[PDB]
Image (cartoon, helix red, strand yellow):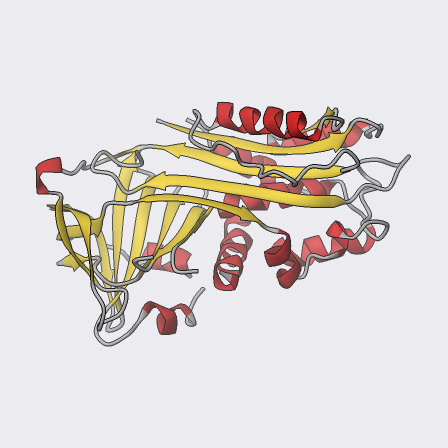
Length: 333
């Protein structure tokens, strides 16, 4: 549980810094995807994986997460031609509640459609078309598709009649008028010279969303180069706040190969060089594409003093495991 939290949060931020005005993804979803190939990898492939996200222990994390709903859709799709080692299929289910499925890549479009529909199922049809065309090819060996579906009501829902459009400042010069939610209520709170830090509970209340709102004459960009830690900000919160935050919708699809390459994971995507001998010994597998989509709303109702009217960072936190389920940024597009 907590043993995973610290390298998970360090991985979360590292990817967040490689990122575009608004950002939204699930560190946990990608981290368990990496977990799957780590389990199946050896040699240099496995070392670059191990050095990236730092035997598991994650089976302790996975058991934490379920029971509103939180559903993981973590899955490898392996070309038909390849026999797959049985211990890997057992461990990936036992310790990660994930699996590898052998699939007919002949008829590339139909396989792609079957996968996107599988992903739709586990995401109550809110993560759809996760695979874009030309991510699968009749000779593709291994693709990883990756998402978490999170639906939860605010502990303290907003009164829709107070949702007034207000000025939001991508930069102190410029301005754009957007719908914002307001209410006055009890919230977790902490403050420095440089930012405010707000906690908004979901229900159940160990699910919370957090916002780091830069104060004073500091922009998000300069502040970002000073974290993360985010997990420590957790420990320091204690307050009644009048909260005004944008009411918005995040739907980010991301092909992660280039970010993960930049992070130091490379052999995994190189044919011939990738070592997935723990998945298939009778043929050379390699990852053509890891694809991730993340959906989430700032809604009066939840997912689907403090005025967040300039750029801010946000993350969705599970206090049980201390896991950063989602991390993101809102800059006004």
